[PDB]
Amino acid sequence: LESFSLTSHEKKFGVNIEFSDVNFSYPKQTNHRTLKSINFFIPSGTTCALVGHTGSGKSTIAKLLYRFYDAEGDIKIGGKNVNKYNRNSIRSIIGIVPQDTILFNETIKYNILYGKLDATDEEVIKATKSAQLYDFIEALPKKWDTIVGNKGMKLSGGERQRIAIARCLLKDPKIVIFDEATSSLDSKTEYLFQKAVEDLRKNRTLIIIAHRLSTISSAESIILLNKGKIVEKGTHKDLLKLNGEYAEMWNMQSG
């Protein structure tokens, strides 16, 4: 098995992603599939939002890109089939910012550099400034050396996810998978999000798993899943005009 390699252009600007007639069920899910005849293509260096009710199969798409499970059908990165490569060379070009990040019981700086144990203090500062985490850390009583985790200072979900964003910028992958955990209790969370997304997206292919549709409206492509099937695809304006399920959700969430 080969090791995945990005072209020089791909390294500079990002890589495309395609799923072709992809079908999956989890090992214990012995009656039904979580994903059904999934076809989509993400152009390199663009953003793609995956939307849909819980159950739709949104997060399973990510797990298959990161090779957590094997699917039937074809997953291709940069036109190349992932089944020709060893898993670790695929994962090295993908960064996950999950809904919920578990912290090591260690300094905040240790938790960040885990993205790339190598990083210079300078790369670490830049990552933490992009993640919107620098003023939070400068204000801490031990700053960098503050012990976090479950013995240690407790961080919100928003804050832990900013560590995850920083880990990811340090990793510097060419694919970023970002499960959004903005809160409709506080509009600063979404503004922080976008500030991060702006830096995250820079010269990368970015997939956003969205639960709140407003985080996603300027995404170059939105894919709406309904029970494992992709039922609609396009940009925000087009999906509203379609007046289908994305328009229904959008209006419920808008009130």
Image (cartoon, helix red, strand yellow):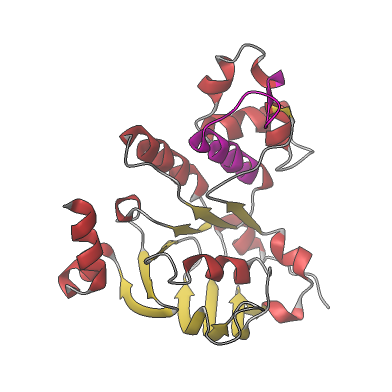
Q: Residue at the location (72% across, 58% down)?
A: 92
Q: Is residue 183 left or right of residue 57?
A: left
Q: Position of residue 41 (x, y in %)?
A: 47, 76
Front in this rendered view, residue 8 or 72: 72
Residue at 45%, 61% in the rendered image: 46
Q: Is residue 100 left or right of residue 120?
A: left
Residue 190 point in image, percent of width and height: 36, 40
Q: Residue at x 58, y 31 (%)?
A: 128
Along the line of sight, the residue nearer the viewer: 178 or 202: 178
Q: Is residue 200 visible?
A: yes
Q: Is residue 79 visible?
A: no
- Tell me which segment is drawn in magenta: 145-169
Q: Residue 157 magenta-drawn?
A: yes
Outermost residue toward the top in this view:
141
Residue 30 in the image: above or below residue 255: below
Q: Position of residue 16 (x, y in %)?
A: 54, 70
* Residue 171 to residue 59: above or below: above
- Give the residue displayed 68% in from the left and 65% down from the top: 6
